[PDB]
Image (cartoon, rainbow, N blue to C red):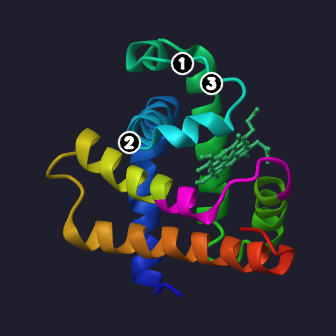
């Protein structure tokens, strides 16, 4: 549950991501895969990437980064009213992709990391607080659908 002020910050920060959605998406996935290599194993089309150089050079990884952040942005722009947007993602990630909620925690923190890296001194304390809350909300609503499905 975010305030309007907080949502305003979130969508303000998001404007940064939208100026370069592929570059941000790329760096988030790279930060995830290198921070937590077990996550790479969930992708049959990235599992071949051994090195970070190969990750950086991967146009298909950048492509998927675009897909992921496009979906997250659509959800964020709903300001919490994202049940229709979120339900199919929860279902596919639980039932088809089999992604534990721990990995959503991982990518949440990775987004925070990337924003500081790409915008040092331009991602203030209030901004981080708002973005973190928004990602927690997202995660918590997925977690509810996971529980429903009995998925661990
Ligand atoms: C912000 C969090 C995330 C968002 C918004 C997101 C969004 C999406 C979308 C829109 C797709 C394609 C449609 C679909 O299959 O439902 C997808 C596919 C996929 N996602 Fe996620 N995802 C997120 C996090 C993760 C994480 C943390 C993992 C694994 C560690 C993951 C694993 C996958 C895999 C394996 C696919 C299918 C890839 C393929 O073979 O095309 N996702 N995701």
- The image quarter containing residue 138 is bottom right
CA neighbours of label 2 inside 10 A, class few (<14), some (14 to 19), many (20+): few
Magenta span contains residue 70: no
Q: Which residues are magenta?
A: 95-105
Residue where numbered disc 1 is placed: 49
CA neighbours of label 1 inside 10 A, class few (<14), some (14 to 19), many (20+): some
- Left or right: where does residue 35 sit relative to residue 33? left
The answer to whether 101 is drawn above or below residue 93 in the figure is below
Magenta span contains residue 102: yes
- Left or right: where does residue 69 sit relative to residue 132? right
The answer to whether 115 is drawn above or below residue 40 in the figure is below
Coordinates of residue 7 in the picture (x, y in percent): 47, 75
The answer to whether 23 is drawn above or below residue 16 in the figure is above
Residue where numbered disc 2 is placed: 35
Assign a secondary structure to mark 2.
helix
Q: Nearer the viewer, residue 28 or 134?
A: 28
Coordinates of residue 112 in the picture (x, y in percent): 35, 56
Q: Nearer the viewer, residue 135 or 49?
A: 49
């Amino acid at each position: 549950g975010l305030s309007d002020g907080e949502w305003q910050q979130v969508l303000n920060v998001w404007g940064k991501v939208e100026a370069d959605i592929a570059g941000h998406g790329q760096e988030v996935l790279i930060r995830l895969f290198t921070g937590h290599p077990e996550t790479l194993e969930k992708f049959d089309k990235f599992k071949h990437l051994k090195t970070e150089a190969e990750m950086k050079a991967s146009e298909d990884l950048k492509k998927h980064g675009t897909v992921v952040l496009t979906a997250l942005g659509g959800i964020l722009k709903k300001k919490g009213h994202h049940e229709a947007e979120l339900k199919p993602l929860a279902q596919s990630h639980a039932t088809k992709h089999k992604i534990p909620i721990k990995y959503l925690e991982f990518i949440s923190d990775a987004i925070i990391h990337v924003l500081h890296s790409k915008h040092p001194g331009d991602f203030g304390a209030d901004a981080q607080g708002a973005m973190t809350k928004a990602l927690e909300l997202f995660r918590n609503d997925i977690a509810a659908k996971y529980k429903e499905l009995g998925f661990q």
